Length: 214
Length: 214
Picture 1 (cartoon, chains in turn green, purple):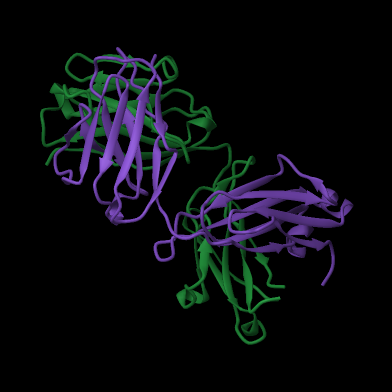
Picture 2 (cartoon, one colour):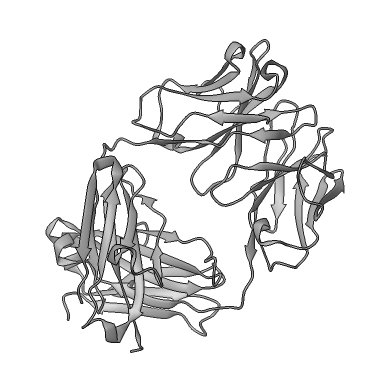
């Protein structure tokens, strides 16, 4: 099977150096160009550069020239992408892809997520979105100021799943993430039913169960 | 130096329907044009190479055509796995521009959002920050304008939105808009209002509260 396998997710601070890898398998790595493509959160694909592993002939896009270094070790079928000084704007998914004489990227790596932020690891602060016409009420938890991703949220230990929406996290200007998880319930159940959001943040070993009362 | 313009930005159709996607190059070049598909949460993959050839393992329902500067991708009858983002790419000497992408999304009937507003919690206020959350639940199409008004004055630069991906069961979107203020600015004002404009509502709908009321 022809494949490109990339190195794991990285979490860094601005100024730090970083080198990520792309390992080819099931084919003669030396014989095909390898391209690097960036995908910023919520954005499209941008070509960064390309390298021919045989002689390390490298070409960069003008937007990336002098900002990153693309290199390859053909002896171990591996291409690399490196930064000497990461920027917060380098936060993106990075893909490596095999280029062919059909002028196309026929095989792609699975992607390497790179998150760059001045923030250090930090558990979230969890606040209620308290329920206050109609037979439906909305309630939730605001999971604020944590880093890095991800957090998981369940309601009543997984017993409440219908009507739950947990929003994608948004990176705030502070470099910390925030999201809300909400649920719509019958307004008549507010006096009777207990609602608890279970929030887990594995990078900080934080777990919070927040009771949301009207 | 060429630009690839994809249209439409969002193509809304149902499984069983025929899809036609467009890619127009600003200049005509001799390199081969390719189409890529990126399913939610996955790496891109090659679909079509040299404008009309299906890549390995790509089903017969995908076809491509065009020449000069006008290219088209067609899916004869959509399957649920085809709802994804599609990008075109064509090399310009040593530069490799991609189109901005077309999102192929599930069309369903128009559904107005249910709108809820949540004041900041007293626990958050004690920490010096106030987050006011506005929830737009289960609406279609995705396009929605959310405007914050504090004492009937329009706000700008102090809010962030997050939108869910299209629900796998009912094909609607949900959206959160969070207004962030310092505790001192929050307590200087009285009326907090979230105004929603959406195709499913005959007029914009506002949800509001007067600070410090039960």
